[PDB]
Image 1 (cartoon, rainbow over the protein chains, first blue to last red):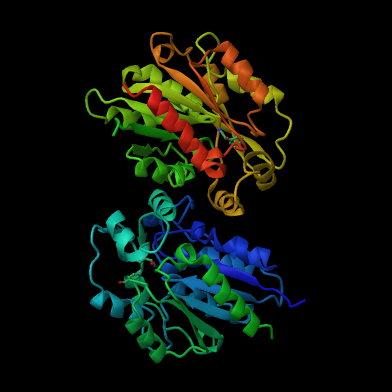
Image 2 (cartoon, rainbow over the protein chains, first blue to last red):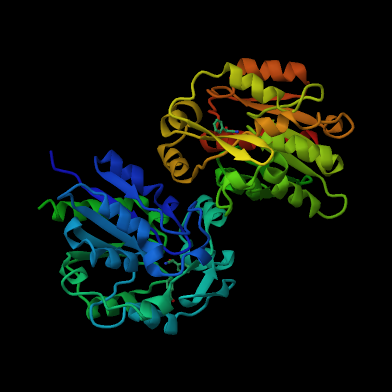
Length: 259
Length: 259
Ligand SMILES: N#C[C@H](O)c1ccccc1
Ligand SMILES: N#C[C@H](O)c1ccccc1
Ligand SMILES: O=Cc1ccccc1
């Protein structure tokens, strides 16, 4: 038969590995292996976000997973939202362990501006945070900006096409997090030899109210991808609102990287 | 249109508030109110179980939920598995805040033997722990026994009638826990004037492979209930395998304590 892949799934800020609970079994039933990474201070990780002061600390469970893969094994690496930044850091360290990067309703950084550039661009134009709570934590690495989503903001901007059950689950599991924008703006730019040499594709939702089309076309313009895929009717949490259609996009990506 | 009630939902050891993610919108969409408590060192709670040495510290978030209710409000308090022990401790403190106790596939303690008695009896009787990992932690006041479920034991004994998604979700969220057996052996008997005075019913799953049919009959013989309800086809995690039939049971119980 056709050969399968190992997908490594990377969640977004304020969430954890649990968001993949629908997608993981569809991928395994089709014969693939799946590793749902849990980032620092996310999900049931024992650290509060105040103890994770840098984006390198945040990403470390991703680096470790790639480090421990046996030699010559390559993965399909999927990053969701802020997970786009994580997957790019990983790519600049272990480029040869990644078959293709999958930017899913994700931030897509480039190899020319500071790594915060696409975050900073969006933050300027963003619109309405609603009942979200902002705060600060002072560290030996400077001031960290934290946020915790409000439930009305979740309902209107992230979960608007999701079953009520998934909305209620997200309320019981989401945590205070950070986009690490200060730390990212001080970081060495992503390299051309690393991150820049890896294959990459972009999967977008049509009804994402966080990352508008508008903005995606701009990120892709600054930094091209091989291919773009579209999930009709998906909200931002597309693995919860349309998991079957996300499965179909990921199979088709798998089939293009058989070689 | 009848009186609606307020349901306080209390999860089992090694799990969290998340388990109620299907049941909560069923109850709310029929007019009821629902608070799903998260216990110490459970779900996304920032503490490890090592730091919660006693079943009073473990139960504190439940106790704070009842204390914050307005004057004269009463709840239907639902306690799943080890949550049966939690709801008993609460009923000994605030008997007048509880319309009825609902022991759902739960440990039902009595007012004659020490509070650890139904737990010690099950532990002598159960032969299918599987890949579950047991350990000790030494506190300033004695040994604290701990456990962490293994995935094969989860699938065989707790989740065997659940959709594969819900078993994947549990594997991403379950944590090391404790039954506090040593602490409960040292604790004073539950009282007649408090816990004993409160109305109680038992709701049981017809295919529970962890709390078997016979053990239930034994527990109810040490300590009578007003009424027993059965859910046909339920596994132990019946709010995940048969949420609509668990909804039907809890509406029937709300109809008997209408007022
Ligand atoms: N990264 C990421 C998430 O999609 C996210 C989390 C909180 C607020 C906006 C967006
Ligand atoms: N309490 C409780 C849970 O149902 C439970 C947790 C771990 C192992 C067996 C049973
Ligand atoms: O505004 C920045 C931003 C970053 C991540 C998710 C949503 C917004």
